[PDB]
Image 1 (tube, rainbow, N blue to C red):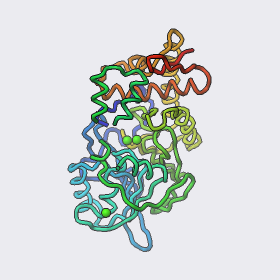
Image 2 (spheres, protein in one colour):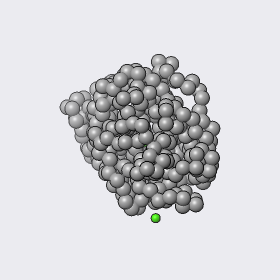
Image 3 (cartoon, rainbow, N blue to C red):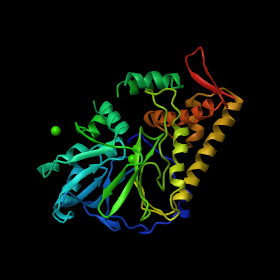
Image 4 (tube, rainbow, N blue to C red):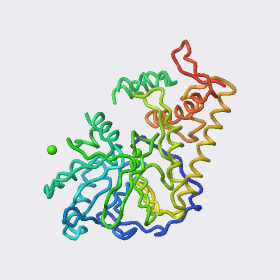
Length: 354
Ligand SMILES: [Ca+2]
Ligand SMILES: [Ca+2]
Ligand SMILES: [Ca+2]
């Protein structure tokens, strides 16, 4: 996420933070609900942290801990995990590792945690959805990205070269060779609770949020974040994708949850106002779509044309191509519902017009 950048929530004051600005220091935990503990790991990106969750649990008579998400494979996060093992687990083992999705800050240390950390203290199973596991395996093991961004309006030969000669493998250095499949609707028994798998689309293949309906707690992964937008992007591998339509449809899964649901997001702070935040995200994308409509009404626009309208800030070449993926997702939503016509110019650039 070094070149990743996000849209900040100016309506944060409409959410409620039950712990205010309290946050667990590195290597320590903070109880956010009975048997649910919050870990905060540093990240070296603009997004400077990820929240991970430790759930008190008992499987087959053995008391211990279920981990949700892992961090990137950095020396600093590994050291913080080791401190946690030694001082914050009450001397009890990890029983299993659940990963919400394959992005590196969530999947990176799965293999290392499954195999017991530096001292190999246990040997446990990774639980994850099939789509996230398989894409993780594909990416864990370029020139296609450059052809992609070129046909969407990036024409500077020097910039295209910087993409050609290009991360995931350094942050996710191994992915477990075995997994336990999570599927939408699965009931997980974790400690005193049943957590249900709520799958989400448009951000990643098959994103797993975990919902404890009786106590009203939601582990939202990256699908609902209080301070930032969720990345929704069209990529070279699925060049006609409609991820924004999938994402906006997916947000309906949370609008039927309780209005007082405690949301545990992967970035930001635990919060209430789930429905408020969903409304803010819907409003945000409606405003971005209106800008795309307005621009395409006056001339055929490429994704590169849309970036400086959608992102009112300076971007380097790497941030530009990341923004281009999100611009293209908004173009594709309008295109595929019949509001734009897609034309590949004789210059090879794909553009969209009213
Ligand atoms: Ca993600
Ligand atoms: Ca191994
Ligand atoms: Ca994330």
